[PDB]
Amino acid sequence: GAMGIRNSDSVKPTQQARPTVIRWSEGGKEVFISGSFNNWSTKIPLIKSHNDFVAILDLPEGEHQYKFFVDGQWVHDPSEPVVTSQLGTINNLIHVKKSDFEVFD
Image (cartoon, rainbow, N blue to C red):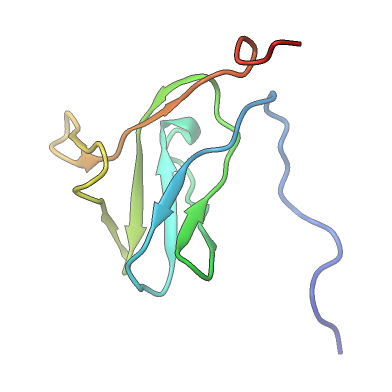
């Protein structure tokens, strides 16, 4: 028998960057996040929290667009900064900053 985990299979070769700010609260079975930060070629797992679902990924300083995927379908929150993509597909909006100037050093 065995429990827990030993080593990881994923990797983070990308450069340094701050975490993303995501918070989804509905009550589905599985929640995933995807945006331009990954070319929408992969679904990032949302760390299920006692409070709600959330996502964490080191993204570059700038503005990116992501989308939620719950209940086996791509959904979005009306409270969040959503926008109708060129393909008529509604997507969320995220804005990341840098900590190079925020620090006094």
